[PDB]
Amino acid sequence: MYDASLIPNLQIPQKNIPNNDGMNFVKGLRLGWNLGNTFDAFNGTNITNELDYETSWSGIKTTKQMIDAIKQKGFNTVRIPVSWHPHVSGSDYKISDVWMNRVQEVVNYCIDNKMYVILNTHHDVDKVKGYFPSSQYMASSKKYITSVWAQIAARFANYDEHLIFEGMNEPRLVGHANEWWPELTNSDVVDSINCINQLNQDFVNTVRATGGKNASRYLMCPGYVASPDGATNDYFRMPNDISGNNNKIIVSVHAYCPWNFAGLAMADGGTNAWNINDSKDQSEVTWFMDNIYNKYTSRGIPVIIGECGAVDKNNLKTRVEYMSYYVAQAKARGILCILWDNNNFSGTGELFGFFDRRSCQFKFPEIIDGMVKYAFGLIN
């Protein structure tokens, strides 16, 4: 049965945030949800045609009713991860119209619900088929980013500010020892960071060049592996935007912190405990948020935590407390949170399933109600 008593009573002091267009835009997004393991799937056991990629990992085709349910809960933003590499051909990386049409269909489900949508490139870090953030691969990487974004920009040219473009997901050195963390002492990672700065710049230039609504829409840019440190380190450089635009670039960060609790499986040495009353455990959540506040939000530059969440370890209460605290602390610093939901309830793999797409209802409602309770308020 639903147990509302699990949700903690929190009164976190609001920090000072500038009253500008950028920060107000983010407040309007309110709280987001990821259409995880869907259009981002890039392989599978039984894919007969290209459209099967949508159900390959998710196991079910997206419908309008699903999106209606998400909105009804209180979410006002849907992030739609898309891996374009298995749907591109030729030296010009032409995107299949069949794939593009389907993506636009799902985007429309959200837009018709007056929601905000974030469209990105996801699992496209591939030396041969996509981009790879290292100097040896800059030629192909630039061609990939510019070709793909010119096409996406042209297709969605008529959509207003409700549609946001996220150039890259978690650009990193796949296979490298420092694939999952920007070790600033490593020569290879510094080269990668510089390459990422260049690719973010190319992404912005390409989109802006198409003019119209593309010239003024908000764009998101991540640092190395979209980590908080990748965005706060001294090597990170915000892209130069066209003259006339002011504060239209949003910093993207992903933070499943602390990892041993939020994502590491029990079988792999993870833990299922996190104490909201323990200062050390509290710090595991706020440390990166303070860095983000000091470097960006306190100064009026928007930041979005595009991915967050905690895997199911048969620890409902602890997860309700953790997610509630996480969202409340982010809100106090003007930061938006977007839940990662992969529809996985199989008891195996990464259990980031929350919304049961089969029955169109949330399986751990207390967690999501706690998040809605502490997210940005709605003025009318």
Image (cartoon, rainbow, N blue to C red):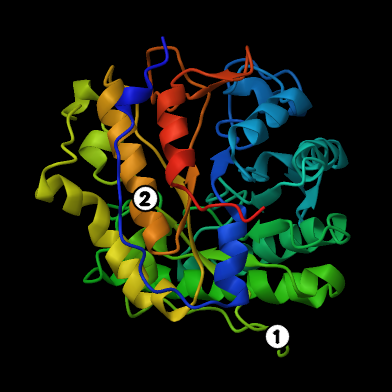
- Quick one: which residue is furthest to the front in this view? 380
Amino acid type, mark 1: Ile
Amino acid type, mark 2: Ala
- Residue 148 horizontal side relative to residue 124, left or right: right
- Mark 2 neighbour class, 10 Å CA radius: few under 14, some 14 to 19, many 20 or more: many
Which quadrant holds residue 198? Answer: bottom right
Using the image, tell me which numbered label, if any, was put on residue 82. none
Residue wearing tag 2: 328
Of residues 205 and 191, the one drawn nearer to the viewer in this rendering: 205
Q: Residue at x 18, y 35 (%)?
A: 274
Residue 288: x, y in percent?
28, 60
Of residues 200 and 333, the one drawn nearer to the viewer in this rendering: 333
Residue 237: x, y in percent?
46, 79
Residue 110: x, y in percent?
74, 41
Of residues 300 and 183, the one drawn nearer to the viewer in this rendering: 300
Question: Badges 1 and 2: C-beta atoms under 8 Å apart?
Answer: no
- Asked whether residue 249 appears in the rendered view, the answer is no
Q: Give the quadrant of the N terminus.
A: top left
Using the image, tell me which numbered label, if any, was put on residue 242. 1
Q: Is residue 100 above or below residue 193?
A: above
Q: Name the secondary structure under disc 1.
A: loop
- Asked whether residue 288 appears in the rendered view, the answer is yes
- Quick one: which residue is furthest to the top in this view? 1
Residue 216: x, y in percent?
75, 74
Disc 1 or disc 2, which is closer to the eye? Answer: 2
In three-dimensional space, the C-alpha distance between marks 1 and 2, rounded to whole angstroms, equals: 35 Å
Q: Is residue 143 above or below residue 45?
A: below
Which quadrant holds residue 113? Answer: top right
- Residue 65 horizontal side relative to residue 226, left or right: right
- Residue 125 horizontal side relative to residue 112, left or right: left
Q: Is residue 256 above or below residue 230?
A: above
